[PDB]
Amino acid sequence: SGFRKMAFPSGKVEGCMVQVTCGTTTLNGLWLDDVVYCPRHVICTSEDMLNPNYEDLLIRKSNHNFLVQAGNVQLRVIGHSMQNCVLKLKVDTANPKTPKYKFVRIQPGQTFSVLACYNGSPSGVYQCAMRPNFTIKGSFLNGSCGSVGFNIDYDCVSFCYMHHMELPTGVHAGTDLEGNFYGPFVDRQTAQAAGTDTTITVNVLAWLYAAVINGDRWFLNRFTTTLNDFNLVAMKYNYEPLTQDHVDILGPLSAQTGIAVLDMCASLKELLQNGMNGRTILGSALLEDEFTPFDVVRQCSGVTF
Amino acid sequence: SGFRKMAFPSGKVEGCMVQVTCGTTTLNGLWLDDVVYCPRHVICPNYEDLLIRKSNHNFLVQAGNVQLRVIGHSMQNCVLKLKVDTANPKTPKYKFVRIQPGQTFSVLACYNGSPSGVYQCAMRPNFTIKGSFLNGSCGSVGFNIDYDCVSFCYMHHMELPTGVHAGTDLEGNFYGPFVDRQTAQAAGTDTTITVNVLAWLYAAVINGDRWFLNRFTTTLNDFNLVAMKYNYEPLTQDHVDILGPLSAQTGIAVLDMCASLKELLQNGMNGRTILGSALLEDEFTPFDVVRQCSGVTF
Ligand SMILES: CNC(=O)CN1C[C@@H](C(=O)Nc2cncc3cc(S(C)(=O)=O)ccc23)c2cc(Cl)ccc2C1=O
Ligand SMILES: CNC(=O)CN1C[C@@H](C(=O)Nc2cncc3cc(S(C)(=O)=O)ccc23)c2cc(Cl)ccc2C1=O
Ligand SMILES: [Cl-]
């Protein structure tokens, strides 16, 4: 029993965090095998940030301009290349603490753990979701650039996010581990804004199934809905459209609790109309959308209360 | 910017988790130096009588794919200490500390000696923790990190009928009036950790959330009467002194912020949220707020 926002154990990722310094800029790098991956803006000055030509800035750098520090040991850079918005520094030592890993690009609504670091040193771990507007509501300060997001399903670490910037509204933007940004963002200090955000509907539904598993049913009703009528109502509350894929994905939770997806959609509809009326669901007075159908199955039991 | 419930990096603790099996019972153990610490109910009650019948080979300790050889055993309160033949090479710098209600810590939840997740939580005033635990989680541990030293403060033992959790410090002393047995036990009525709600209101002001601030101030005596009416823990002069740095950083006196909390209790949020919450959050200490709004590393 119980339902917490839970992050993956960060140990396998802590053993990969290094500090990358290029001139006056210092940020974090991810050391896997004999390569250190970090944001390419480490080669920029704050001036360059408005309209930087990364190819022109990089061609003027030599291997010895990059200082890579792994704990108290200095790593020797023996090569460098750029892949999209990520800089790849070939080092002379392979990381002995390199875990089994994959680079994965995630879709909006997917969750992951973030290991926030400063000066190549991990400070904290938290769980978050890729928002529909491609931003993450993280907790990052200056020096956090290069911190990574990951999932550890089985003994393999799937790296999905590398932190690059904070937007004017306080939300965060970054890339996959191949340097491709999530969202229409650029690694420039230019006027950029996050688009209007929406609630991840499939995740709120998953969280309502987690509440039923933990013995709470006060929000259920005797009604059902069509998929289209659900979306006509949900769109008015800034909720993402629920697709047939989402319905199929909620199948196992529907079978475990005996509550059809469209009947759970009717409870959601009524919750949006009525609010909670002094009640909470899983200790929350808001409808939670940062737990996927997969997270709920992982954290909750197989026997409903 | 941003404010998340943040746990300490779990790496130093992951390297200490082992699986302990005794007969049919399987739970988690903490391997530090040449000793494995685990709940004494793994032998299940008259514990000294159950223990005297057991021999070293009855205990199966597994560290990853390696079997550890038990060469001795003793009991300390509600914790079983299994002397093993191998000292843990991944043993970090550590201390066993007992925490007070209101203090927070990270929990590394494990099943079969394998860490599955990490979360942050607080020791409630009623000595329970609102954790996320399933069967097999017994022996999971709670900790904080101070520089490079891990301070172990909690070991999981049981789930109460309301779904909340009970456990001990690493010396086997329970937090709360609980016993390690399946008997009629219930968590007492809980209260809100006032100093923590105040700390979280200062974190909101730091992140640019000031709609709840007012021109009023109050006295500690007047505020404590309001706190008693809403099931909030009494605010002490120590709590006020502890909030000093946050008061200085934001320019808002502690009794000035108390008057805001007083108005939130009597009138609600009115459709508004603070740090993305429609409830007053009490699981961030004044220290957690300063650490997260500064960037302290380990
Ligand atoms: C909020 N940012 C700024 O004012 C300046 N700025 C610097 C940099 C950037 O965003 N770094 C940061 C990353 N993560 C959290 C950050 C929190 C802060 S703070 C003190 O807590 O506001 C400051 C900076 C952060 C950057 C990188 C790129 Cl690729 C593109 C643009 C920029 C940029 O605009
Ligand atoms: C709710 N528990 C029970 O019905 C039986 N029970 C077993 C055991 C105990 O509490 N273990 C558990 C610990 N943490 C989470 C647990 C979640 C669950 S569940 C399937 O997800 O409901 C079950 C058991 C859990 C225990 C240990 C001691 Cl020292 C004293 C008493 C007991 C005890 O009463
Ligand atoms: Cl995905």
Image (tube, coloured by chain):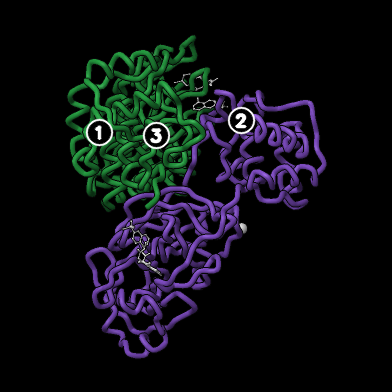
Chain colours: A purple, B green
Q: Which of A12 and A288 lies nearest the eye of the viewer?
A: A288
Q: Chain of mark 1?
A: B
Residue found at x 45% / y 59%: A172
Q: Are marks 1 and 3 on the same chain?
A: yes
Kind of residue at badge 2: Gly
Relative side of A64 to A162, left or right: left
Which residue appears farthest toward the front when viewing the image?
A: B215
Mark 1 → mark 3, Cα distance in angstroms: 18 Å
Kind of residue at badge 1: Phe
Looking at the image, residue B145 lies above or below residue A62: above
Q: Which residue bears the numbered disc 3?
A: B121
Q: Residues within 10 Å of mark 2 (few under 14, many from 20)?
A: few
Rendering coords of residue A180 (x, y %): 53, 72
Is ligand 2 less than 8 Å from the beta carbon at label 3? no
Q: How many marks?
A: 3
Looking at the image, residue A114 lies above or below residue B257: below
Kind of residue at badge 3: Cys
- Which mark is drawn over residue A275? 2
Quarter-of-image position of residue A30: bottom left
Rendering coords of residue A71 (x, y %): 26, 63
Q: Are marks 2 and 1 on the same chain?
A: no
